[PDB]
Length: 195
Length: 48
Ligand SMILES: [Zn+2]
Image 1 (cartoon, chains in turn brown, red):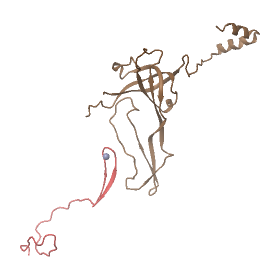
Image 2 (image 1 turned 180 degrees about the vertical axis):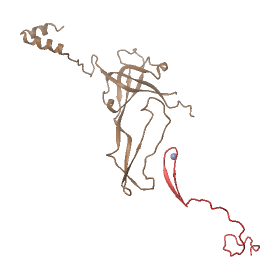
Image 3 (image 1 turned 45 degrees about the vertical axis):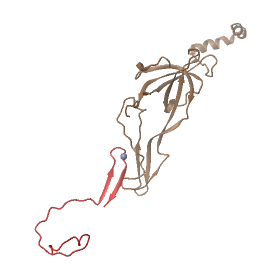
Image 4 (image 1 turned 90 degrees about the vertical axis):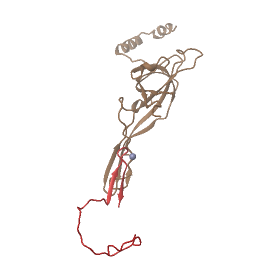
């Protein structure tokens, strides 16, 4: 987060640091379905925003339908609509790689749908994603709004930290682990190898 | 008569006689209008 500058915007990057805060997982409305009792018909609509497509589009600000093309009143069908989850997290440079006595640097990561609940505050993490500039930096009237749209989130383990360490076991590894057992001095061999 | 019209008879009912010399073509005028917004897609109606 300290060596990430304005010359790396619009490129895929890997960032190291510590997770300092996570927000509440909220639903996001995509498609909404309705019912008209005067015609027995169901209607739908779609919604989109700027944080779902990597390229810039022309905005379409559609509205929430309460009324039919003739004027019939519509009932909202909450069970038939589609919702997708959302979360935001903040990353900061790890305390044992940061310069002593100096204030730290941080970066915002946006996660959606399946990557929404993978970490907790106070974790070592590695994130990969696109470093995006958003909106207009006051030219319609500080600078531009910058954030990472996450695609990969890796938990990492370090000494004196709440993330556990696990390894993938190969069948070859299993064979040695199981072979060692039969010999009746397992305790001594494992004990003498402890520091 | 047609020459006996003055400021008095304005917003009032009169009875008149004469001869017809012109008749235009029929024009179209609205009575019920349905509309939509080109940006947000809001719909409404108008009655005349
Ligand atoms: Zn509008």
